[PDB]
Length: 49
Length: 116
Length: 24
Length: 107
Image (cartoon, each protein chain N blue to C red):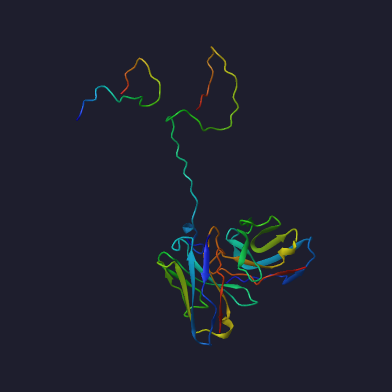
């Protein structure tokens, strides 16, 4: 790591997010407001992804 | 917890040579490269040179080239600095320094005054 | 000494519910 | 080589008021590749700001640094009695890093 060298050699911080899907009940998800559930009609639902 | 104790002050005649040591402890000596800075009394700081503690690759200053030489003892976790053919105005407080948690400036030593 | 383990050690392989079906 | 000049060698100010320091460069320096130094009398120099905007650990919020390219400025909002020391500017954008000559604050 040289700070006096060419730019393609200077250190970069990399974080890799690896996702395991279907492996267990879903627990990590974004801020989405929920609503009440309506029965006996075809509705476009989203249950834990 | 990190402490660096350098060698004592030196008084010498013009043209001679001087070597200054600095012992290191509390960190992996090989992991952080060492840096040397000179500061004459009343003047500013001037960087002296670099030597990595892993492989020993070299990058000296043009002004001081042909007179300065750093070596490190990994077993004793101690850094050295050899300087030959001194002149009068080179009388200064000599610091050893490794960057830790900072790009530069970390761990400046207690200083060694070489009087020529 | 050794014994023979008969019809043992079966567990739910995938935690997904299935019924009235044969799954490999 | 890039040379540094700080316009005020010493600033005589009563504690409580506004102080400003300058330190410019001759050839352009990346903003990230910068730091700022405070060297107490008889103690090793201490990094006040690095990255030309970001403080180090244990630095009071009264300090702050800014600037990019060649011209750089250090800000001190409130002068406390212990703050009276010497301050060094340093850039390490390319090859040899060059340090400052220092600026003293007087009561």
